[PDB]
Image (cartoon, rainbow, N blue to C red):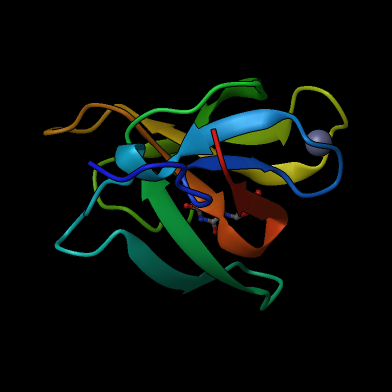
Length: 111
Ligand SMILES: O=c1ccn([C@H]2C[C@H](O)[C@@H](CO)O2)c(=O)[nH]1
Ligand SMILES: [Zn+2]
């Protein structure tokens, strides 16, 4: 529907690893963008994706402090460089699983 789009793929900002695509953004509670803080007070602009790749999911899930009701999280690192890119979420409903990735740790560009 658009020739030569420059904004279709998300890659790891620190190394280039393919991570997700704009077509895979997922509006959780009506918005694909959720702004949250961890217990250390860090603010994150979290983009929700249905699907992602090139990550490494660390350990087992935890429900503690989850920003998304009904889901447990696993830390998602870039599988190539180890940069912490976000979290994989599971154990919930409609959808069962998704990714919440930290927007400013990704780079957007052409396929
Ligand atoms: O939904 C989530 C996912 C992660 N964290 C925090 C917990 C932990 O301190 C750190 C792990 O990335 O992020 C949350 O607060 N909520
Ligand atoms: Zn990386």
